[PDB]
Image: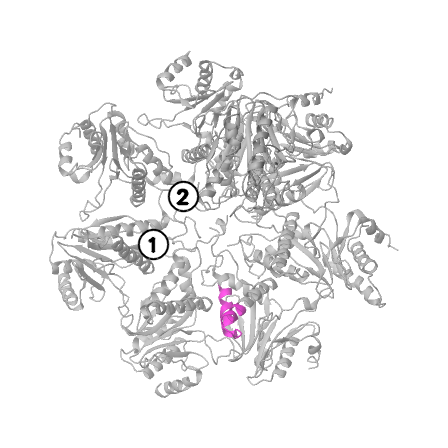
Amino acid sequence: SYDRAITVFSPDGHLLQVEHALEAVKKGGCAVAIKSSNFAVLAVEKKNIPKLQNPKTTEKLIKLDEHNCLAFAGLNADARVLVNKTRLECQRYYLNMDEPAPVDYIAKYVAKVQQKFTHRGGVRPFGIATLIAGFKNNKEICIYQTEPSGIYAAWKAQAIGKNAKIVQEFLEKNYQENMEQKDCIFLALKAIFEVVELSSKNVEVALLTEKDLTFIEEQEINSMVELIDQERT
Amino acid sequence: TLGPVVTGTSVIAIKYKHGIMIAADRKASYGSYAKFQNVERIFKINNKTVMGFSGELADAQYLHELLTRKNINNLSEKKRKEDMYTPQHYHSYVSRVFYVRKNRIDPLFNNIIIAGINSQKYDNNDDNVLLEEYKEIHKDDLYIGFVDMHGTNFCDDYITTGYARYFALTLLRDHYKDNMTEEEARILINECLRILYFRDATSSNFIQIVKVTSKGVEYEEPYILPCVLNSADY
Amino acid sequence: MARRYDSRTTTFSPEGRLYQVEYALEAINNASITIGLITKDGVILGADKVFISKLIDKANNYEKIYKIDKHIFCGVAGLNADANILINQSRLYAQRYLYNYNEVQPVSQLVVQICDIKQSYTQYGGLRPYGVSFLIGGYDTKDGYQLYHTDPSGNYSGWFATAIGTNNLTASSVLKQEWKNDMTLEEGLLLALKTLAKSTDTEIPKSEKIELAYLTNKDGEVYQKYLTEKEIEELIKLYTQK
Amino acid sequence: EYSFSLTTFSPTGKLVQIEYALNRVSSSSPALGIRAKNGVIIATEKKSPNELIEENSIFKIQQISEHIGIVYAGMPGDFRVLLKRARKEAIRYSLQYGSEILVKELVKIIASIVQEFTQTGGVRPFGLSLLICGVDVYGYHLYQIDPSGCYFNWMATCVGKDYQNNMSFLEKRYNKDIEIEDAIHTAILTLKESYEGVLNEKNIEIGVAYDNKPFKILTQNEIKDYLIE
Amino acid sequence: RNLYDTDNIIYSPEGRLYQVEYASEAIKQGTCAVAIKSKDYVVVSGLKKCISKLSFPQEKIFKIDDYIGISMSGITSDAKVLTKFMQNECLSHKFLYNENINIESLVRSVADKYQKNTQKSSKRAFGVGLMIAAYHNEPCIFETRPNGSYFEYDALSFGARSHASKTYLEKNLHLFEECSLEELILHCLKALKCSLSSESELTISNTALAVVGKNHPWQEISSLQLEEYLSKVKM
Amino acid sequence: SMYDRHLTIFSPDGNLYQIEYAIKAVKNTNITSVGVKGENCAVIISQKKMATQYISQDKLLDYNNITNIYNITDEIGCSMVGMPGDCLSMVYKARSEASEFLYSNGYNVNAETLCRNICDKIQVYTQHAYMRLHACSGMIIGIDENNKPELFKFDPSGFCAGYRACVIGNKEQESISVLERLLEKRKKKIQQETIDEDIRNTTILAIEALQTILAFDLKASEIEVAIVSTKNRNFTQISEKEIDNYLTYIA
Amino acid sequence: EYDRGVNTFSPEGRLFQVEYALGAIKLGSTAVGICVNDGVILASERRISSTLIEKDSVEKLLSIDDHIGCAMSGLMADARTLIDYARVECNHYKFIYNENINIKSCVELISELALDFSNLIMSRPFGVALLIGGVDKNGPCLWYTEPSGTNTRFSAASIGSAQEGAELLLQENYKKDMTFEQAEILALTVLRQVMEDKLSTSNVEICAIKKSDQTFYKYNTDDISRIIDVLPSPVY
Amino acid sequence: SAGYDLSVSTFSPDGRLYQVEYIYKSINNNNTALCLECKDGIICCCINSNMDKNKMIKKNSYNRIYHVNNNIIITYSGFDGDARNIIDRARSEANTYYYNFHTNIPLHILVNRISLYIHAYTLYWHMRPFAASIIISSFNEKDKGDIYCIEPNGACYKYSGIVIGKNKEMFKTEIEKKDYKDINVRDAIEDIYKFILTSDDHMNKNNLQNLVNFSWICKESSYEFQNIHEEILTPALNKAVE
């Protein structure tokens, strides 16, 4: 209804309307972010019907500011409304502080607004799990995983979305400390479609640096994919 | 509410040994024109308190409604004789409303005087809002409060407001002795009102003298007689 | 307290879905079919008129393909009643953008506005969702001809050809098998008839039926719509080659 | 917590509350609208009442503006609130633009109000169907508004009880170039055949547009001459 | 029963508001508190609750104004709302006017705060009962039930084993003439001990006690002062 | 859900059972009020009896107070029959409209506009589920600007038909027959020279109808009539001294 | 919730939501606080889900103000809004009144927000358990806020999944008089008995609020090592 | 009763409005209240029978006799909080009348305004209907007194003497024995005690100087509200019978 608590404590102590929101994330698309010395790479899963549905949906890899990534995973309906609030927030902060919003501040806000929607009355919790890549006040890259419950934490290399457990356990065993520009692409690609089909059209990968977020084009994407199927043989 | 076009005049309140004695002319003037000469400017807002008057009549009539219904609300929620509001309580209530209006710019031009007996040692726990011997009051159980339209509030032994604050005040400040008797208070008040007749244009005879004693609130209408000083010679 | 009387229309299901949106999608899967097609000349929208009676005026009106702006138009498939609520809303959005920025609103920006309002009802408010989803084809000077397919849930997607409505699968199959990337306007119109005829398993359309419209920008965004007369030639042409 | 929709999608994808409202519209007295070459006819049958009632005090055919009439078939209470609210739109429009409102914009405005009660919380859908007819600079019009809020453009229609065969009767007796005088003749006949126990006098009602004359409601003197045949 | 319980609006077929009858027994779980009214003194004592032998005893007695003090018994969070309301009410009256708030009028002002949370369905009845003990010009004790209701007493008891403490007070009529607070404070402390369970914790220096009277503003009884009182209780 | 408890929700047959139940609530009081309309004269009758409710019936109530007839303005009167609380609330709403209409339009409300405005609110209850219908059906009489009588009845369901011989109560199923029959006698009498004969043609007609609708004797202290005929136009309650005068025309 | 709202008394006198939230505070990592007469020490388990996490952004012992620090239990995301709220209220107090807030006073404003859903704005009870401590005046203080809103000052409390075991150990090994160092080694021993295999630096985040300096201090990897080496209880 | 008795805003199929008759059994299990007219003034009565086992209340603290404008007695029998809400609203209306009209509100419209305020709560989902039956009385010289009883759900009815409460059936049958409109008010106090001693089910027995308290508005009170001084109660306690 209008102004009723729809998220309330189950007799065992859990919040059922948040627990169900987590299961809405699992029915999404996997997203992977990898950190490095001074840049972060983000690779996500995209689904397009052949010959139709031009890839202008560009769900994941959302620009927030000059240097702020966002690769959500969950209900695309709630993705736009949550993202647009941050973009509204990012400029307001850059107006009240005259300095671009750091990655940590944006993650704290996204975690705040998400947790706000599971505490107010007559509002459904966001069915979205996001991860943000950006630079702090000091120039230092960071990735901030987020959950629909509002919990957030910084991660070196985290995977969210559909069957993120399999990707995470793989990503945990072969992550180097400071990988190369072409290594981070490979690790993200090798991990993103460990659960996704090996086709190069399914994955969309972009790399974030100190300036001018760069989208990786299909040339090397196809090139590295052909380097992975032979890895699987 | 904006400009005092229908003004009252000075009222004089002194406390004598049997209680409060407050007097006031019964004239309200339309500027320089004595439009009404039988209006009363001393209201009874409680069995033991009375309310003064000066300046605009509309504002002081509106203020009387507030104090009147404040009494009845007290009277409804009254269980014993000690629950009744003291004259000091109304003074601190009139002070607050004048001040609240002063923060805004609608000050309801007035110089209200609140007087009465601030004690319950003289029994009146039988209230007839709609219709023996005097006692000696220690002069500390009597309250005579003043409220300027800026909110300036204070209490004293003889509060003269309006225009008697220049003539009657000098007489009282060198003649008011403690524990004045009944008729001695009146001859002192009468001497103060007579001067205002000669020296105030917006004043008149036909005084309304109200006394607040241990038995309650009284009323009577003299016709004080100014005629002195032999200016007739030509 | 009407707590016992509430339906909790904005509450997650045990499997992480929303039942109200789940049922709204079912409502728009029983409505008349609508076809979208992008050609090099322009974008084609053609929907099927559900038969009511021969007494319908069927001369100067049809309730499937409306006009949202001079360069944007939509083909509705779902509850016709609340479509006019969103059509009027999107008409307001496309005209207030022009009020602020002094230029026509790009299609990709109107859709996100009309999808945010469509989504907002299933996020908070305790109200039922909009049981309506419509293709929104339009021409914008930035990214040319576009075609977007909305949803009661609020999530849209760009497309080259989509066939929402009843029996959409049999109309997406024919579109997927015959939509050449580069098509002329008359070629696309024939394709629209073929997918409309096959979706409702009729060999030939009747022209008291499916209606068609397009943009075909001629540096002035002509935005023409068919009266029934022009479709006999389209029906004649389909018969000759099929 | 007191504003939540009572009209919700059923699992089979139908707004079941609307289907109930249409059930009651399909059980009221048949209203009927017919448009001709030079005017529009809206007709309803008001069942033969007791002599206690004053027949003129209740009229299912009310007038919106100079050239826009109306008739309903549903709950009389909702017609009055909708008719009164419909007249405000016809006046609010004329308070901005000089000319009298035209039917196409009036129907769209009213339909948006019928739709609101379908969606907003704590209220029920309107239990009636309207037939707004009028004369404009764009010719003659005859629209129908469902309880669902969706509106249709008609050349001839029925909304009341047993409108299935009632409208089938009109299909075989209606043509685009029908004379307005013949339209009333057909309008009487279709109501006459549907009305069981045919006593179609003192229990019928006609409203006519008459080729850009002001909308007029035929009093019974002007009706008995139409009951010969 | 099952149907006539969900909301604070439905009346049971016997005309009983269950959702305020249920909150009326939340006070029956709080620890005992006893108020005794003398000729010119009021003595309030309450048993503090220790949830563990590491935790500090929970505060039971609260001060409202110079001569007004209370002793809640119910839900602690609900009481804290009422003490703030009462404190902000006696202070405003001492600010708007220069008098002391009429204790009879103050209780009514807080007794209908219970009420406004009973008409609506978005609110719940306060789960706390109060013991408004004050000396305005005469000693007086009040008690407010979760349903809008208040009474003036001569002795009280709250909840835990109040029936045991009431028996001690119900049979003692001395309290009216019990001058010499020493003789009166013992009467209250003996009453509080009566409710206290045997073969368990005895009344120790961790039980609240406060007084208010003619020229005695609301004051706690200091532990050094309180300690000898407990000694005479053992007698 | 199965909750046809809502004030508005259409039942699967298209009916609002709450409207039917609210109408049943008016019948439960079994208070019958009859008003008939004549030539430039309107009269209205009620029963001056306790509404059939939970409280104990008449023992010490001063029966003068117990009336079902109120007046809305100096020239408009009404007879609300239903739950006593709702009837009292209905007149205050009715009084405000006629007062607001006067201030906003500078002339007294018509007897037909007042009830139409009343029905426009009773519809709001019918359509908003958050509240409940007033179980009150009232009859309103008055004189229009053409010096013609007006009689109107509204229902818990918003419906403002307006009759020329109306009955409200628990016997309207058959009272429609007698009132129709008994009103034809004044039509069979075609003298047509009744010059202000409301006293002996209309008031007596209405009292006869009440004596026939319900078969008691109609003691003058258990009925009351009110007439807004021309030459009065004031809705004055007719005194008991001449109510039993008509009751002595049983001959 | 099947036919009940948030404000509903059980037939036993207890509220339903708050007695349900009490079961939500028995899942967070164990935190142990000890209040001696020289300053409060706060210890906390660190449950690193994976080695990929940075172990720094995730934290358990924040600081409400310059002289206050707190622990957490239960819904971690639901506790940040309290600490953020308390930070504004603590700072707002320092502006209106020039001095520092009492920990007892800081807890009350947190407690009253914990039932803002009750409506005498949130909508459900907060499901956390705080362990606030500080050194305002009258020596150091240590409090403990429940979802039910009741707050009891403790001398040595414990929160988290293993709080029942930690309070069992504290309730025996705690003495009223200890030096600061005796508290530090005591807190680690309590955690060591209930934590996992390794008592490493990356497992606890002990912070102290000394009475002398009157300022919280988050122990770094160096200050935390010299306390583990003590091993006052070498029992396996 | 099959689910129609939950909320106050639902009519049962037999028309009776439940959730209001349940209130009627709530007041009818409450302490009785009495009010009757004499030839000099109204005398009221409240028998606080439920407060007999407590033995701790102050002697004459509890009092259900309230007055407004010092010349209108208001007493109730029901929930002592819900009724006290109305008294403050009754006083508000009296104040509102005086601020506008310089005159104490006439009683016959005070009962009308209170009847609407009480009834206004019987029209909604959320609002809980009041559980108090209100007795209002006033005496004048030019016109004798009059008593109104405002039951729940409006229904203000003018009486010449009424009892509301638990034993109102056994009190009325004893009051109507004598025409109190010709009986003096001083000696009517004796009569009502004989009813309290007998018609009360042993709740009050020879120790009732405290349980029952009441007041009149009579000539000896100058037609203004006044509780009877204790020096008049005991002479009326010459109840020694059998």
Q: Residue B140 location, x and y as percent?
A: 51, 23
Residue extending furthest top?
E235
Does F65 sit above or below residue G43? below
Q: CA distance from mark 2 to mark 1?
A: 21 Å
Give E117 or D48, whichever is nearer the viewer: E117
Neighbour tally class for label 1: few under 14, some 14-19, many 20 plus, Cα within 10 Å = many
Give H212 or D89, whichever is nearer the viewer: D89
Does H71 sit above or below residue F35? above
For label 1, the SS is loop
**Main SS class of the magenta portion in the image:** helix
Direction from residue A50 to residue H114 in the image, left or right: right
Direction from residue F45 to residue G193 in the image, left or right: left
Q: Residue A86 location, x and y as percent?
A: 29, 56
Give A104 or G46, whichever is nearer the viewer: A104
Instruction: Name the mark on residue A126.
Output: 1
Residue F172 part of the magenta-drawn span: no
Q: Amino acid at mark 1?
A: Phe
Direction from residue D12 to residue F183 in the image, left or right: right
Q: Which residues are magenta?
A: D89-115
Direction from residue C92 to residue H221 in the image, left or right: right
Neighbour tally class for label 2: few under 14, some 14-19, many 20 plus, Cα within 10 Å = many
Instruction: Name the mark on residue G117.
Output: 2
Q: Amino acid at mark 2?
A: Phe
Foreground tag (2 vs 1): 2
Viewer can see residue E37: yes
Dot 2: chain letter: G
